[PDB]
Image 1 (tube, rainbow, N blue to C red):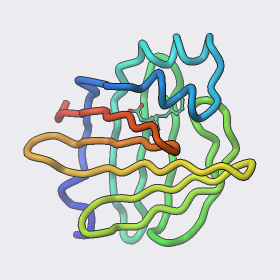
Image 2 (image 1 turned 45 degrees about the vertical axis):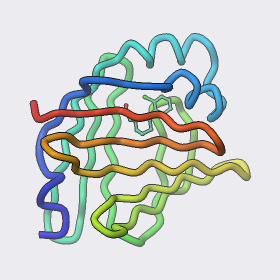
Image 3 (image 1 turned 180 degrees about the vertical axis):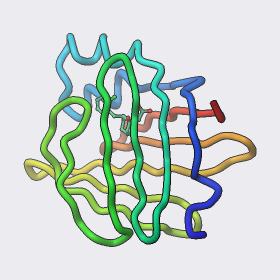
Image 4 (image 1 turned 90 degrees about the horizontal axis):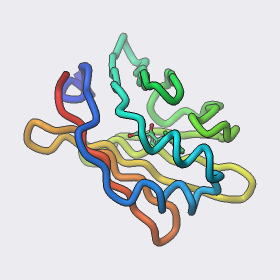
Length: 133
Ligand SMILES: O=C(O)C[C@]1(O)CCCC[C@H]1Cc1ccccc1Cl
């Protein structure tokens, strides 16, 4: 019941500062422009200890499955090959990605009827707000 309030199908309804986040991560111009148009569906499910997060989008479809606290390989929507670890901290899913000596942290939280995704790279934050589909 660990992630019950996250489970479901969610649709992006607003974004702030995403272009700058992507720049900070190292995403190139064309990818930033195409990725920034997308309005993804995020589908979160749990089966036993395994959490699955899918992103269905006109840009890229992605899928990760993981156990909390257990590192895994991830290929991100912008084609970084990263090592990821996701934990639950005070009810927030905290996702750290490491690659090439760099790090970014993605927090996913339930706030009212929304699922808020906060993406941080050094000093740069982007906030992505999802609602139930
Ligand atoms: O789409 C989102 O709302 C969230 C997201 O799918 C997971 C968290 C990180 C940002 C984003 C992935 C992502 C990362 C770099 C370049 C383009 C993209 Cl699309």
